[PDB]
Length: 16
Length: 16
Length: 16
Length: 16
Image (cartoon, rainbow over all chains, first blue to last red; front, side, top):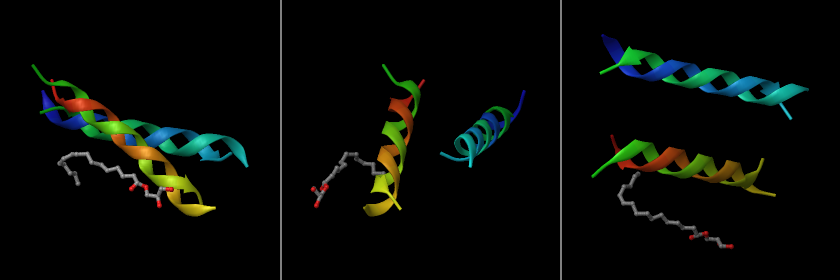
C-alpha cells in the first residue's frame, strides 16, 4: 500500500 | 537539534 | 532474501 | 566529519 518504505525521509526529527 | 536525522522513519509513504 | 531497505544505516558516512 | 550521516543508505540489507 502506498509507496517507498516507511514515512517521510530519515529517522526521527531534526539533526542530532 | 531535535532527535536523530531528517523527518519520519524510512523513506516515502507506505511500502511499495 | 532482502531485509528492510538499503545497505547499512543512514545516508552517507559520518556526520556532516 | 565525513559526508552525510551514519554508515550506509536506509536501513538493512537489500529490500525486503
